Structures are given as structure tokens and as C-alpha cells.
Image (tube, rainbow over all chains, first blue to last red):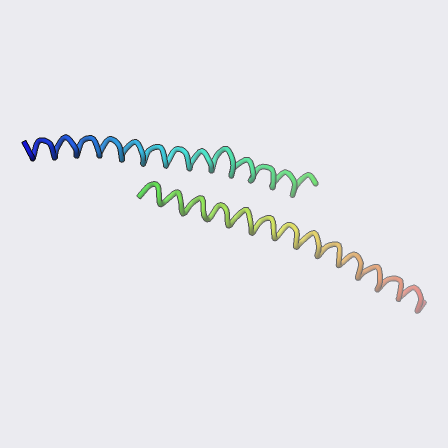
Length: 50
Length: 49
């Protein structure tokens, strides 16, 4: 029962840390793509057109 | 590993914003200073003539 509870807690922590890592990666990629990338675009437009 | 890899990616990206903005400002200032120096050189040459 101790090992079964350990496996249950392992599965719970595994799914929790998996969703945490996934959320971190997509949120940071979203920061790159919707904040950093528009800044790249604005900087390039300012350099070229102006 | 993926998280840290594209974290290094975004860190390099932020360095790239900073470097690109600094380079653009520096080149604009350099062009303006070159124009002013050319103006000084040309008006001195005109006075000499």
C-alpha cells in the first residue's frame, strides 16, 4: 500500500509537473511570438520606413 | 530541456532587440554627425575659395 500510494503520488506529481512545464513553455513562446516578435516587426519597420 | 533551450533563445532574442536598437540609433547619429562635419568642411573650403 505504501508503494501504491507512492505510485499514485508519482502520477499526480507527474501530471502536475507536466502541465506546469507545458504551460511554462507555451506561455514563454507566446511571450516571444506576441510580444517579442511584434517588437522585432516594429523595430524593422521603424528602421526601414523611417 | 526544451524550456531552457528556448529560454536561451528568448534571452538571445532580447539581446538582439537591444543590439539592433543601439546599432540603429548609433548609425543614425553617425550619419547626422558626418553630415554636420561635411557641412563644416565645405563651408571652410568655400571660405578658402
